[PDB]
Image (cartoon, rainbow, N blue to C red):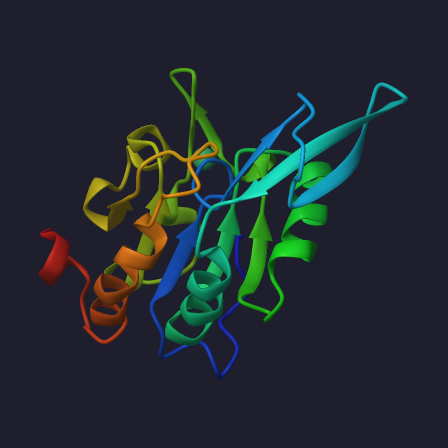
Length: 180
Ligand SMILES: [Mg+2]
């Protein structure tokens, strides 16, 4: 069985974009951060720890627009119990049509790989936005790299990628732009 159901009517003409959470859209820590965007309590072996979450600058604009341009899918190497609460707070617009977590990755040579082949979408119309090439070793021709983000409040990578996405949203075959 594929990782996604069939695309709903309003999504099936669109390109599918698989989006990484950590160091791509947000950055989370167990070290207390003053003036955090969100704090989520995560239970680990019966004990609750606070996870301090910072949003990358421009992520609201980015997410809002990507959910129009694309069938967006959150595909994180992290675990639902941290990633669901975070996505609930982040995704104000219903941008993420599905959420896929650690179990849905393939652990390959010490790396959590998003294997786009198990999605159930024609690979000519799938993109992956990820801060590490390890994320997409199987699909390097589907990828749009973005630098890892931690706390640099002057970052504008998400803002500056939007026009490129704006363009990719409209092609028929992403390989015609990325090359395969
Ligand atoms: Mg990441």
